[PDB]
Image: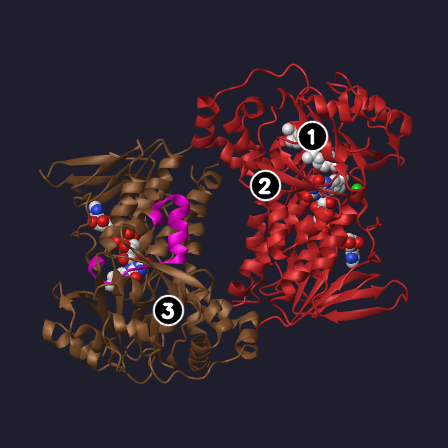
Chain colours: A brown, B red
Amino acid sequence: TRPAHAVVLGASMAGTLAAHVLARHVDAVTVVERDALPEEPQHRKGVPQARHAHLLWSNGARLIEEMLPGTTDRLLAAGARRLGFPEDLVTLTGQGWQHRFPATQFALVASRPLLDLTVRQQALGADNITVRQRTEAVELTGSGGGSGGRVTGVVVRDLDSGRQEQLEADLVIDATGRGSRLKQWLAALGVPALEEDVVDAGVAYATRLFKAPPGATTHFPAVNIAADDRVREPGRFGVVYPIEGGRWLATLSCTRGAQLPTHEDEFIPFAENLNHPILADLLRDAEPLTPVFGSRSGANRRLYPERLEQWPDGLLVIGDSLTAFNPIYGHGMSSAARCATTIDREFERSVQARAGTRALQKAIGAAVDDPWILAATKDIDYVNCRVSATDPRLIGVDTEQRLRFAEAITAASIRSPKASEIVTDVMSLNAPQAELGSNRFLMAMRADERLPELTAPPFLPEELAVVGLDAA
Amino acid sequence: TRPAHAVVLGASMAGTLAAHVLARHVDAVTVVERDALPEEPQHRKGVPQARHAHLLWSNGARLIEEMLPGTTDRLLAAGARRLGFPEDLVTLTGQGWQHRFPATQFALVASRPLLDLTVRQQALGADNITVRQRTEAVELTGSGGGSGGRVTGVVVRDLDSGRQEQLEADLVIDATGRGSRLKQWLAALGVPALEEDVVDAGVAYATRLFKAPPGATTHFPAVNIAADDRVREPGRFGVVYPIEGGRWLATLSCTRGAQLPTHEDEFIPFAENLNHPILADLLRDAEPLTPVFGSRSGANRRLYPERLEQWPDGLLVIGDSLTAFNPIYGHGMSSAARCATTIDREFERSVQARAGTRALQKAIGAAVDDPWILAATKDIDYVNCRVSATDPRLIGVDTEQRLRFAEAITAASIRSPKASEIVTDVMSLNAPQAELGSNRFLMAMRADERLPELTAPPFLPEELAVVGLDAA
Ligand SMILES: Cc1cc2nc3c(=O)[nH]c(=O)nc-3n(C[C@H](O)[C@H](O)[C@H](O)COP(=O)(O)OP(=O)(O)OC[C@H]3O[C@@H](n4cnc5c(N)ncnc54)[C@H](O)[C@@H]3O)c2cc1C
Ligand SMILES: Cc1cc2nc3c(=O)[nH]c(=O)nc-3n(C[C@H](O)[C@H](O)[C@H](O)COP(=O)(O)OP(=O)(O)OC[C@H]3O[C@@H](n4cnc5c(N)ncnc54)[C@H](O)[C@@H]3O)c2cc1C
Ligand SMILES: CC(=O)OC/C=C(\C)CC/C=C(\C)CC[C@H]1OC1(C)C
Ligand SMILES: [Cl-]
């Protein structure tokens, strides 16, 4: 028989999308969220990464727009910018500057709390969605111990007065995030441990927001300094994106072995000593609007509940709980949208005992494969990267065959339009990484023209006039 | 390493589409076809079903259009018709006449040889495709059984010289259709037998081609008398479709226990003994252009190579060879297009592991589930139906509840616009059969208005004037 009540743990991107989707297929859905959610855009305790740069790649954006029509126009009215790639960015790769070919993909950029609010408003207004704020999931209950267990509900605790309630339900959705209490709950029911691939390059972040020169958030590009160097030196990177309200969101990052700015005054010097100091030039006369924010949530991890024979019935794991990625590639929100979309597309087909929630988690795991293999492939080669994985695409691979080809892909994408186009398809999560090994790509990479190398960041003169730096 | 040479066995719809797709991912593609392929739209021995009415549902038409842009316009310029459902059809169901709501789906209708030629012209002109006509696939080469069987190529025989030749290949695609000798080729290699579901209502067809009254193929709807009483009485059905050249293709059908016309003078009386005699009224004075053609290719059957642990590497099976349906629901060509589209989307991901073909075949198997479960569900309850299936959606099911739910779906779709729209999504193969059990459908089915029962076929006066009738 069908699930009549579903409870989703978490009201971040994964849980909000899953709640809306499950509300179409289940009579009642209740969402459990620890924080209070404001109806004006504010940062909150449960989303600590919201202080850092968040790009909603076109894959996630289109999937959210299809589930929740009007969300993008709504975002555009609230001041978000639709950055076209590679056209609206000044990007330095390890092979040189990206030619700003006419945009072949896009990403929506705005403050993460604004996007979360916009999605929550579109998604949680259904009458069969009850949102229980200030409520925490303690552990889950079920008929475990193996032989083919089932999850029956979740222990919740109200946070304004610590009274508890055993939340009983036909299906439980773990969207608690990267720090989620899933593997301890799995232990508490006696189901054996999951298989887990890890590629951890130890990426850490440091973000500050500035007030952009008037008109810069519309008439000036974003700037991204990314030194590809993996196997000789820890990476150090920095990016500045425009957001709503005429403000620049500046995020610095590095890999294990390099050290981040932690004081305000050492921030710009990190931007100063990148391979080009363009970020420091932009940030010297901007109004700082925030302190430094830090994050060390930089590992690629992936659990494979689809591989375990004793995966309990009635339980699903989505979002950062299922698999989390190096944020440098910006796929977590698109991977979350894929999980909900997969649920929407396969729900009725697989609930037709629940021998079908195996198929759901199998479908979900297949939906998150693209952002996993993308991030892990690029991170596996960093010095000081810590790896514990079974993926034959990573481990059964000549490391110098991957490096030489990684460099060649990059060199093509910065100066060949047709290779740039396919590479942005992969980077936007609209084509699998394997497409970069396809006959089609290898043909473009060889047949397409290659423009001369850019000897300076490809700013247009009028763009430097908006931020007042023409001598560059 | 990656496949460099692929051999496609059969050049009907499944093999032509698969060859076109494979030529984009593999250096060389050879197509082996027993028949000579005409450069004019002509019938041929290898596709005898082409004598009968063929509908290309929007699912297949859109997938073909995306693989081969311009195919639809080229079909329409050659005289194909775009039939909107339900608007452009006068249909009698077991619950009454379908209200001709504004079209929510469509199908392209033309003679199958015209559709085949147009597709082959768009698809087989790639320069890395070699088509070996008048050539027969005799057997496969390789080792089978054990921990790792593989197909290495194909023994072919030229039919004009009689000479044989071992065609080596990295990948072999069986697209030889319902009469495919794949199970003997697997036995000859030592592969254990496949699991196979069958739901066989003994469907048969009898078709004649007629000259339509002038203008009827553009200004007169198709007509479909499709009223059953499955569990008490064999089905008897009839359809008249317009095709190119001002012609009507009339296909009568019945299930096991009823008798089809075999002689020309028995054709109109079968149409007369349908629940409404409109088909006989339309055809009585129409000029017949052919004798009666018959077909007994009416079983639903599905092989599950994706379930076989000893499925050999380098082998894929698609099209009617993998799974074939009762043609009354008209999904075989859309299922073929789904197999080719799946190969296009999953190929690169699945070669970068053994030969990658187990993952492809599994993806192919999931893509053919929609037409299988639809056709099998509708046929399973016919009197004298032969059922040999392990599908739990079919076998573990209260049959009076299934008949009771089928009747209710039909009664809703004929008289409620919102129920019609969802049913046409399912019937056009654009939403799974399971959607008819969703909360969305059950609520649409109850909340929507229901128009009055039609007491006569919903022809317009102008349409009855085109064919010279005053009242059905
Ligand atoms: C530095 C950084 C930068 C990133 N940049 C990008 C980017 O540019 N683009 C992009 O697409 N993604 C980006 N990501 C990833 C993205 O932020 C996440 O993948 C996304 O938020 C999806 O996570 P989630 O919703 O599954 O979980 P989370 O966002 O981590 O949310 C978990 C939610 O569950 C709640 N919760 C947790 N435990 C409990 C409990 N026990 N009881 C009740 N409630 C609970 C929390 O309060 C919270 O609301 C970035 C991540 C980081 C760390
Ligand atoms: C009566 C009837 C009506 C139908 N109506 C519809 C409809 O309305 N809509 C729809 O979508 N589908 C319809 N179908 C189904 C549709 O005809 C098939 O699904 C479609 O042709 C795809 O089949 P295929 O390419 O896999 O195989 P086939 O069309 O059967 O082609 C097999 C090909 O392989 C070749 N071949 C066979 N053996 C060998 C060998 N040993 N070596 C080399 N070549 C070989 C044959 O010559 C042929 O070219 C109908 C089918 C029937 C029987
Ligand atoms: C309601 C019900 O009974 O199921 C749905 C099927 C119907 C109504 C048959 C319409 C005929 C169709 C599409 C023709 C298919 C093609 O094979 C021929 C040659 C006839
Ligand atoms: Cl036939």
Residue matched to label 3: A376
Q: Position of residue B432 (x, y in %)?
A: 53, 39
Chain holding disc 3? A
Residue at which label 2 appears: B429
Q: Chain of mark 2?
A: B
Q: Where residue A382 appears, x then y in whole percent?
A: 32, 78
Which portion, as a residue range, is magenta? A50-73
Q: Quadrant of residue B101?
A: top right
Name which residue lies at 19% across and 40% down.
A133
**What residue would you read off at disc 1?**
B385
The CA distance from mark 1 to mark 2 is 24 Å
Please tell me which residue is depicted at 35% across the width and 36% down the height of the picture. Answer: A23
Left or right: A35 in relation to A451:
left
Question: Who's the residue at 20% across and 60% down the image?
Answer: A51
Q: Secondary structure at mark 2?
A: loop
Q: Is residue B409 above or below residue A347?
A: above
Q: What amino acid is labelled 3 in the image?
A: Ala
